[PDB]
Image (cartoon, coloured by chain):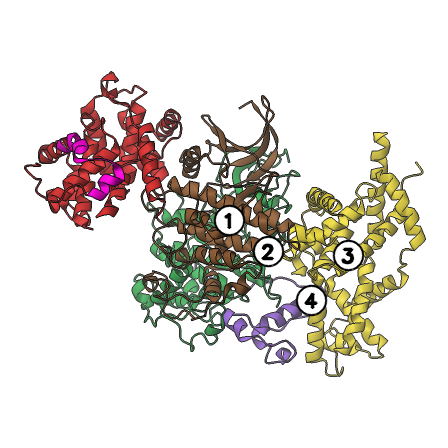
Amino acid sequence: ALYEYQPLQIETYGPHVPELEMLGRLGYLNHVRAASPQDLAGGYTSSLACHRALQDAFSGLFWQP
Amino acid sequence: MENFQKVEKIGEGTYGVVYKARNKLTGEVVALKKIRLDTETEGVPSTAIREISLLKELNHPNIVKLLDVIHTENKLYLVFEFLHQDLKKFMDASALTGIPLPLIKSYLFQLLQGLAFCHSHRVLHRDLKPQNLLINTEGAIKLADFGLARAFGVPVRTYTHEVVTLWYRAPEILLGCKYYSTAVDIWSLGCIFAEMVTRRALFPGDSEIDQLFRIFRTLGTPDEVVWPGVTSMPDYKPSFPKWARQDFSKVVPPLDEDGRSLLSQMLHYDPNKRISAKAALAHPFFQDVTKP
Amino acid sequence: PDYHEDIHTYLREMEVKCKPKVGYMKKQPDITNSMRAILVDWLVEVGEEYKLQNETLHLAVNYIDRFLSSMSVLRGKLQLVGTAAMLLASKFEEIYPPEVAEFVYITDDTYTKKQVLRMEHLVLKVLTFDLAAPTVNQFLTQYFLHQANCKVESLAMFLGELSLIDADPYLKYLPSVIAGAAFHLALYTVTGQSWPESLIRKTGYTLESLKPCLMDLHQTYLKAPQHAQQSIREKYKNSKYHGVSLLNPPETLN
Amino acid sequence: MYHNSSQKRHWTFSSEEQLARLRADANRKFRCKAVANGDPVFLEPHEEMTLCKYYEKRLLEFCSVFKPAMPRSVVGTACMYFKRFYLNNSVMEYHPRIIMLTCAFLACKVDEFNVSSPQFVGNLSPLGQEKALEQILEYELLLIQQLNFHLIVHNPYRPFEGFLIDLKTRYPILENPEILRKTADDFLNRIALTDAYLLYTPSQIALTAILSSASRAGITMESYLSESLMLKENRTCLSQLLDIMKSMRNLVKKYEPPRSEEVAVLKQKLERCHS
Amino acid sequence: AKRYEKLDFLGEGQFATVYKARDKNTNQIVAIKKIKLGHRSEAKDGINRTALREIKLLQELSHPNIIGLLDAFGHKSNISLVFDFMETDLEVIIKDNSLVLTPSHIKAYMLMTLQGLEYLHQHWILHRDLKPNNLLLDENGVLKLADFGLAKSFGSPNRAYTHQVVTRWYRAPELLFGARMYGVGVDMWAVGCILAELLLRVPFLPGDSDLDQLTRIFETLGTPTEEQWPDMCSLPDYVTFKSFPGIPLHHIFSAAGDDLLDLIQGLFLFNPCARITATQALKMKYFSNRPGPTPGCQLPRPLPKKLIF
């Protein structure tokens, strides 16, 4: 039985968050602090911070206890 | 076994549990280290064997006394004289006011006497850090925690897993030297001397490379003149940045001329040229020592 | 170093307290000198197999001699005593000792792991944790600083190890005397020189004082090829020790 | 993440009636225990609530002056620990001063704000400092146990920043969203005083603060919810969102700060209870 | 508390003592870790920070391939953590030469490791301590990532990162050069090393110091230029090395196929931004190719001379 990839399906109860690779395409990266060359050497990009902030903003927005 | 009453649990290391306990027949308070010989697939830990065997022979005022060893089929008890606190806690508490200079000199004199006694008995402490130096209320300081100690009747190999913490590691160890020597203890003592004087770690590196670069930045990047044979060491790289030594007038401002000369001799790059414990005891820095 | 003389003096003082009882062999109702020789030879072979240092072997032999000096052991438990002594020496001296499983395996599972652990506990109880024993290896290392020929060093080490096999003539000599005699013999064999004056002033041993152990060691060297135990020579045949085992002993010694 | 966190699962309650029931149960339980051990000294639940409000303000003022400067996340975590702990326990069993010091200690440890114990007690007579450290060390595990070992706390600050980024990117109707920041921050602080942390998600709180600040400035962003958040497809969800935001605003409106003299009287009563 | 019957001993160490116990309520075997107090210097810190880290991170995760924290009781002095009982780990399987790791077994182990890691990184958490002895296994052949004592959340620009790196054999080169900001690459590199171990039964890059570890990395894979690592020289602990040529990957792993070689190359890319992620790794053709992974139930389960006197 061969393996087939299936994406994680976790309900966030909120608005959809754009994919990480598209963040600079739609212009989100225009409003975050630029990464230092040291950060890029370590592998830290401003896209990570932008995606984290958006995901936290839209998480559990439509949920009721 | 039943002669001691456990007052409380003091610590819990890699192999044994340490209690503060009381001797029922005498009333003296001791530190009882219990190592359970059960649950061990190899028997007595080799660290405990080396510690007991070396500490039995080291009878000095400035070394923690191993009063008794109780050996049982499944438990092993080590009785030490109890000292309430270590020098690291004392330095943390006495920050922002500073340890008095006479106290620092007396502490260094006592530590040097203890280390010289250890070295003349072919014993290498290998773990000289402020957390392992225990003080009492009478103004005395003792070497403790002989868990990494080794006898060097034959040369001792360097082990990556057993080694002092980063801040007090000597540069020869950082560059991958094959064998230990007595000069690593002197380097650690010099680092502790500087930390006591300036209330902060002399070389507070985050990693091995960072620690090496901090040493290079303070004392200058070594070359074959100041440290012969340095370029042949296993971890030496030709491309190390060439910093210049900054004079000891700023690394340890409060120290005087004799203190600065002693610290510079303790912090020699060359292990062979580094000052010894007894030659350091003969220094003019210790012309006026009195226990406070 | 400035502590070197202090270390030598401490070793000279400490070799007396760690000296095994002389003549304990005839107080043992079961085991004898020949069995001890086989045991020590097997210990040499085991140390070779697991790549242990020579200091570990010297310490193990010292522990065995000290342990047999106050306890009586049946001939079936002698190898267990040797295994426990070697394990203790490995724990004290090696950078990391071999596991107990390897030790019980090297004796083709003659004894269980529990027996090995209990006998190690018994040896520790008998010795009272006094395991930092001066050896011939340490005194030879101390003496080598007064030379610098590597062949002489290897041959002196070979003779010092040969002194371990026999308990009859060598158990009455301190390790310092044996090391001095071995150094003199190696110097005479390779370079033809004698006991250097620096060593006389350092140790206080003249030629006359080293003479008895000197002829004992020379006789041992002469009859080494015919000796029933040969793992020491096989150990020193390697180029790592410069192959000094297959050298030519001096037929005379003046 | 919040959407599958322990805070959502176990520490977000349907209404204020649940919170009142839990606090009344804690008070009555302590009264029963005290009367079983062996009458006008016990504190009613509202008095306990007033004392808890006062000590939360005290914890805020303690964290504001902390050296080195505490990040906002640590302060939010400490305040949430305080609220959760006194949801199920009574002030007359554990003094809120030790409890808030322990909450700050635990928050610093959890949020990776590395400070040693001497630095922590230096922010407080030295003898009182060592006594305080002893009490904090004693009460740390009790506080962890009463939190059900749910230590990660989700705060509204990161959702607020994410909302600001989204507004700058996809809402050009608003010229400069940054001017909305300061006022919104003030509203957030008011939210922190009420019980809204135990009733709503952090994203809801952040959005409520942002839109309240916008409405105070005379700007309407109904289109931002309807269009940018795609809520015109699901009108019911938009309705619930507006009701939740209105409930939060009313909760802020009805909040009454503790009175000084009443707090002093109740402090004397609680000190007598602990004596 | 008092609901567990200790019935074995599983190990000791610098941090915790692990034994095996019975739940006495559901009659299920669990593992209890008692957290030691450490040296007497660290006697006024309260609860251990590593224990708090493990508790707080594991209480917010629930995946088949991540160890579960069943309970976290504790006496007011000693705190104990209760986990599922796992019989072995990957290190035992790697070091055991009696059993043979077929390609399907390796694919299974890698697949479960990557699924757990993808779930982990989706929640903005880095494990930071990946090695074969932290990948536990049970009787049903289910791998679980354990030992979350170094794990930390990433994404926030705060530089709370204070060392706490894995054992140097699996440390990524950007961590060896002292990076303070990083992402998922630090996990992925370690994964590659683990994969290499599974392919050779010995550690891939066994250095004895940070400089020696970097030397071994650059000798095996070639010294990176600025084309493959654009900002490498900006790292705080940067040291210039010789221009080693590097060994071709198919020479190191002679039995590996082309898809496996592509996966290994992706896992060992010097640029941390270009290094593949767990999601990208799971989508590679290696995993969907024949043969499929081994089912969890079928995974493997673990002179001289006598002297006569």
Kindly indicate whether the residue at mark 3 contacts the one at mark 4 (C-beta within 8 angstroms): no
Q: Find the magenta span and give its range.
A: C197-215
Chain in red, by letter, is: C
Seen in the picture, residue B117 relative to C81 is either above or below; the reply is below
- Please name whichever residue, C229 or E197, is drawn nearer the observer in this view of the structure: C229
Residue on which the image places disc 1:
B287
Taken as a whole, is the magenta stretch helix, strand or loop?
helix
Q: Please name which of the two marks, 2 or 1, marks the residue nearer to the observer.
A: 1
Tag 2 secondary structure: loop
- Please name whichever residue, E236 or D74, is drawn nearer the observer in this view of the structure: E236
Specify the subunit that label 4 lies on. D
Specify the subunit that label 2 lies on. B
Seen in the picture, residue E136 relative to D223 is either above or below; the reply is above
- Please name whichever residue, E252 or E259, is drawn nearer the observer in this view of the structure: E252
Chain in brown, by letter, is: B
Q: Please name which of the two marks, 4 or 2, marks the residue nearer to the observer.
A: 2
Three-letter amino acid code at the position of disc 4 = Arg
Chain A colour in the picture = purple
Residue on which the image places disc 2:
B199
The CA span between labels 4 and 1 is 62 Å
Label of residue D62 in the image? 3
Residue ID at (66%, 39%): E76
Q: Specify few, some or many for label 1: CA neighbours under 10 Å numbering under 14, 14-19, or 20 or more.
A: few
Chain in yellow, by letter, is: D
Q: Is residue C213 magenta?
A: yes
Residue on which the image places disc 4:
D158
Residue E229 drawn at (x, y percent)? 45, 74
Chain in green, by letter, is: E
Residue D216 drawn at (x, y percent)? 85, 75
